[PDB]
Length: 206
Ligand SMILES: OC[C@@H]1O[C@@H](OC[C@@H]2O[C@@H](OC[C@@H]3O[C@@H](O)[C@H](O)[C@H]3O)[C@H](O)[C@H]2O)[C@H](O)[C@H]1O
Ligand SMILES: [Ca+2]
Image: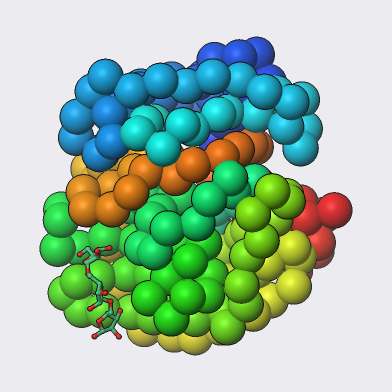
């Protein structure tokens, strides 16, 4: 049972639209998820045109993008800088119940982070470079969670929080409620219902 695709934010057309047509387009935020006045440029990315994030800007995605107990997220990033706790994909029912794919987390490594009630540490023990393209993916199947870097599985575990089942949660690229906005390039955002097979993974990564 391969994971089913639901959303593809590719930026290929120099806009924040979902190419599958399922979801409304993304918005532009200021330096947090809940504010406005940012900027988004478009530069050559991993596939076609990628989104540029200047370190004070983000993208609001539509509420309820993920709303199940079985889901996955894939994307490419090219960091111009790294800042601790700063999100890529995020992630939140409210400020106390959130998920976050973090390039440099509290242990200084890439991690899938959830908090704060409770706290989940999805530690990869792997560190991301600036000025290079890294592929990141992760799947959630009823508490069963796995994290992939460049196609390589680095974290697995269980008892992941069901943050999204029953909630109209806020989703964003590059910003949250507390930390520096991501700076650099984000490309090819894809959302899935169901947990990506290893095969789909290695495909997406290469
Ligand atoms: O709630 C949003 C996040 O809170 C802020 O916390 C500051 C840093 O987060 C903590 O990370 C360590 C966590 O606490 C441990 O119990 C658990 O193992 C870890 O997940 C550190 O205390 C602070 O450096 C962040 O700014 C924001 O992302
Ligand atoms: Ca693209």
